[PDB]
Length: 321
Image 1 (cartoon, rainbow, N blue to C red):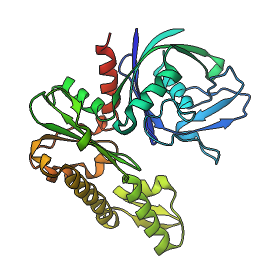
Image 2: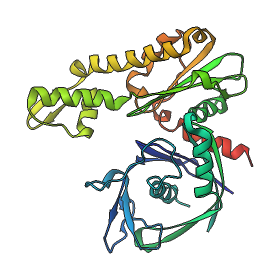
Image 3: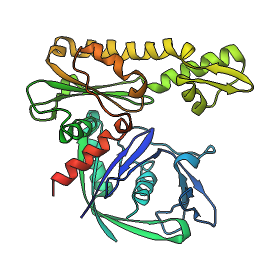
Image 4: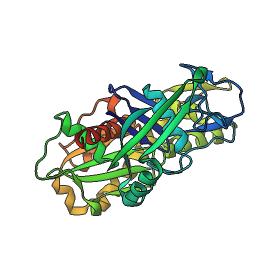
């Protein structure tokens, strides 16, 4: 059997293919009425209904009937389905499949139930570049709560260890920060100490954009404002942003997440033995979180930040065989 990892974020879609191959693309798609099947290796055009409709996904999906997931791990949504298909296309494998995936703890059982009805024992038939048809018979979906995936990956890599005490996975996304407190005894979530905060990197990016527009007269594209968090960039022949101006914004972002986690954990913070910053937002502010519990910061490679959940979803799926 082929085991794949899948994590359909509202921001990015991550897949770990049969050989461990890591693919990441923006979680967006748009209908195209093209007669073509796009360009293999550059801008694939796919169909899940044999060419009744077609779509482009990822980097090159733009325009203004762009479609995005309305939240993380909504595998049964109609917004996710094209991204699942693109993920399977990108993995490069009628093939029998077990998918390991996940979704936030908050709506775990509902989303799991829905994801199973939408995907389990279904055949996805995807057409792509040169009219090639690939068939994927999803025989089993195995699901873990978001954050648990990351903690399992780190356990399997020897980076953390089962013991008494709590690990706190802080997943800084673009619009949310998903905080998963896991019991290291049994790798099970502590529901009362896990929560989603409605703040993320996007808040900093939007604060920087607003501040640029306010002072300069015109509007940065989102992609450029994100870049401008980490270095100065040019728009309309003006130098704008970089750390001198993005620093206090990023600092406010870290401070608010830290304050909100302190509030939620209260005295249970004394039980924390590992703090585990993941997600793309952790690349910029992740080290600040050590001040929640000094000496507990876990060192995660930058290139694992966005895939740690998917890797662990894949691991969990392999162990159910």
